[PDB]
Image 1 (spheres, helix red, strand yellow):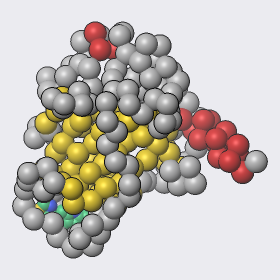
Image 2 (cartoon, rainbow, N blue to C red):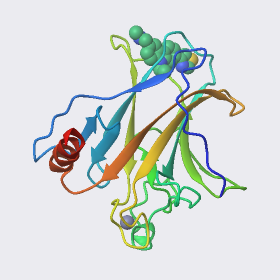
Image 3 (cartoon, rainbow, N blue to C red):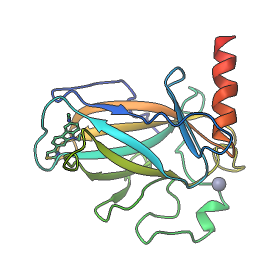
Image 4 (tube, rainbow, N blue to C red):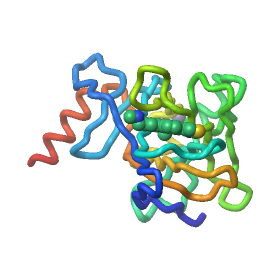
Length: 197
Ligand SMILES: CCn1c2ccc(CNC)cc2c2ccc(-c3cscn3)cc21
Ligand SMILES: [Zn+2]
């Protein structure tokens, strides 16, 4: 399959992501490394991702998430759930069981199987922040481990977040690496130490 672009693009509205500062304690379930541009999270746990813009986008703007493999020798392979997890009937009623990325708690989430690339994505309406908040947060879930045999099988992935107009045209783009693992705090600490070395 052809490879969706991962080029960072703020666009007319100044679109970019933001992440909480959750730390690296052994008990943490989701933590983001700015130095690695990498999110570490446990299986199927809530991953808050912030959306930031400098100016107000039009009604009908949407926000899409898609995963691709990071390594060039694997980027043409569709990222999907492994043969076990696609069959474990953990459906939320909306997400197809094959999809790695879900949006949590948004009844207007839509899930796409691309008719030409066969790639999976989940898209929601772009919404302004809640009254009293400075940004909008989407809660994502990753539904396989990076290590799952027959699926990602230890290959690193990226999530690409695109801001789109109502036709699906590109307005903005950002991305981050993801590792779905049992101990995100320890793994973030290890990889940041490896980077320092
Ligand atoms: C991207 C999320 N977001 C913000 C994040 C951050 C900010 C900046 N707050 C200091 C504003 C917005 C914002 C405004 C409007 C809309 C909107 C209108 S009609 C559809 N979507 C969305 C907004
Ligand atoms: Zn799996």
